[PDB]
Image (cartoon, coloured by chain):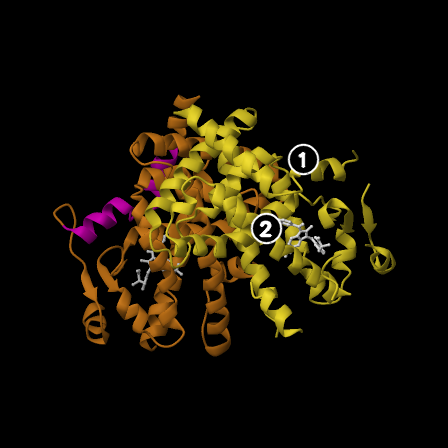
Chain colours: A orange, B yellow
Amino acid sequence: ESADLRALAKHLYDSYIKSFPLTKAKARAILTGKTTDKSPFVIYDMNSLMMGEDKEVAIRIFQGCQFRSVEAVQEITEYAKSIPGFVNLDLNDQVTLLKYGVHEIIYTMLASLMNKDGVLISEGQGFMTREFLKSLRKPFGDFMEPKFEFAVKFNALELDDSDLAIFIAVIILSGDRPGLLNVKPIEDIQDNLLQALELQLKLNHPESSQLFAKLLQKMTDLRQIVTEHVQLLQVIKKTETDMSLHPLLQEIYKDL
Amino acid sequence: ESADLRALAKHLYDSYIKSFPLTKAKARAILTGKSPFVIYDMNSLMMGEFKHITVAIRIFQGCQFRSVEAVQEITEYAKSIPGFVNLDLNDQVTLLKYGVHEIIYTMLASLMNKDGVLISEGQGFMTREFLKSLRKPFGDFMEPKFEFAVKFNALELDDSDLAIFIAVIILSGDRPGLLNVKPIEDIQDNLLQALELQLKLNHPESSQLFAKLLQKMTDLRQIVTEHVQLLQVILHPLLQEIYKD
Ligand SMILES: COc1ccc(C(=O)n2c(C)c(Cc3cccc(O[C@@H](C)C(=O)O)c3)c3cc(OC(F)(F)F)ccc32)cc1
Ligand SMILES: COc1ccc(C(=O)n2c(C)c(Cc3cccc(O[C@@H](C)C(=O)O)c3)c3cc(OC(F)(F)F)ccc32)cc1
């Protein structure tokens, strides 16, 4: 059995690497220096932002993240297909699982690109500071803060990509998502993912007491970030009527 | 050291039994025949017979009265948890402040089936349908608890399981304003260790029960958040003081 669970962990890590071009390991090598990777150009004010790119600031940056989210949903969707059992589920439920799982996964993986000071951008080529994001115009200045506050706590667990691979899989296969037709097949997959995760954390973090429990508890903070994020999008759509929002992102948010 | 975790487990069950008059075992007995007055509509409610009487408002007032009683039961229980009373007193207050609602909804689940909720120490039964039939926005007060309860109860936890789970909720190191997170997480790790051993022993046939129970903590925080937004509204002055939170 436990040999089977190591095989699952290995499968998931493999697909993760295949699906997500900027891993936590690459992110950390960029963020902390040095030699395997290269140093980011740092955006920290209106000056550096102009010198950095080679209509207005906050909205343009907002469209930037909006476009990254779309790529992220594309990568996540590719990864979900690799989770054993996922593609065999009722198609409606595949859609439901992705619809609800995707943003919880975006914020988990976004934490890999973050430290307390800011976030990696343009595939690790850039680094935008938390302060600069926080200084942005009235509604946009609030978008990233909750993600930074999560990242700081989440990053304290010291998870690596092989851990995150299984964790993200656990998130996607939640049998407690609204409007799931066949809850049981989903729960049977998740049960196995949870077993695999537990063994993986035991093995990878032997000195780390109750890391499994401490990680599942983080799923609480993920839910709150989603709620807050979609509230701000409501504000943006009514205040910026000329603002375009990607169809993929359109039908994900609609009917939380 | 798993004989010490069975000790902790037992200590916590012992205290829970002391602290909460209506146990899950007791409530399930009442709910599945082992007889309460039933409240299903306006006329059986009027006949039904409370300490809070000073329709939708009277029911909501009753729920708040009961919540205030429950806070003190939970406060008494928290004192039993090895290490809790040795915490900084501000942190004890913080842990209780943010944890009681989560525990109220957890424990309310023990008193609910999909059809209604035991009321008044199990002497009564208010139907789920009577509760949603109430005027807006009072008919939306209790439905999200029934949704959670039905899901939660499907875990089939017993009182000795819940005694440890509730302790785990109290000792959460992520409450805002905690001054000394270390001993709290130190205690909770112990309790999580005890909870895991309890569920392995009490439910050997359900593999990731531990995990599934911990995933229910997100459903709980969600519920508590939704509930406090419904409390946004948008009275006797002394009464209004008793029911601040
Ligand atoms: C698959 O999981 C993820 C994949 C990619 C990313 C990612 O690269 N992102 C980055 C660096 C960001 C941060 C960011 C900030 C400012 C501008 C950005 O656009 C450009 C410059 C870029 O990074 O390519 C990007 C990001 C934001 C996102 O929207 C949010 F979830 F926060 F609502 C979504 C993904 C984001 C995060 C999670
Ligand atoms: C220690 O945790 C608990 C202890 C007792 C109870 C409980 O008996 N309650 C019942 C049956 C109820 C359900 C109920 C419905 C209508 C009137 C009620 O008031 C009286 C009749 C009563 O429960 O004694 C009670 C209850 C509701 C509460 O407010 C709420 F959480 F829902 F916001 C709080 C506690 C409630 C719940 C949790």
Give residue B215's position: percent from left, percent from top: 50, 43
Circles 2 and 1, Cβ within 8 Å, touching? The answer is no
Residue drawn at the location 20% of the way across and 53% of the way down: A31
Residue in view at x 61 percent, y 42 percent = B152
Q: Is residue B189 left or right of residue A205?
A: right
Residue at the spot x=38%, y=61% of the render? A146
Dominant SS type (magenta): helix
In the image, residue A173 above or below residue A256: above
Residue A167 can be seen, yes or no: no
Location of residue A2 with respect to B124 vertically, above or below: above
The one of B73 and A120 positioned closer to us in this rendering: B73
Q: CA distance from mark 2 to mark 1?
A: 17 Å
Q: Quadrant of residue A152?
A: bottom left
Is residue A68 placed above or below B28 in the rendered structure? below
Amino acid at circle 1: Ala
Q: Magenta part of the protein: which range?
A: A11-33
> Mark 1 highlights which residue?
B25
Q: For mark 2, what is the residue?
A: B104
Task: Provide the chain ID for the residue under circle 2.
Answer: B
Q: What is the quadrant of residue A116 in the picture?
A: bottom left
Q: How many marks?
A: 2
Closer to us: B137 or A130:
B137
Quadrant position of the C terminus of chain A in the picture: bottom right
Mark 1 Cα shell of 10 Å, populated few (<14), some (14-19), many (≥20): few
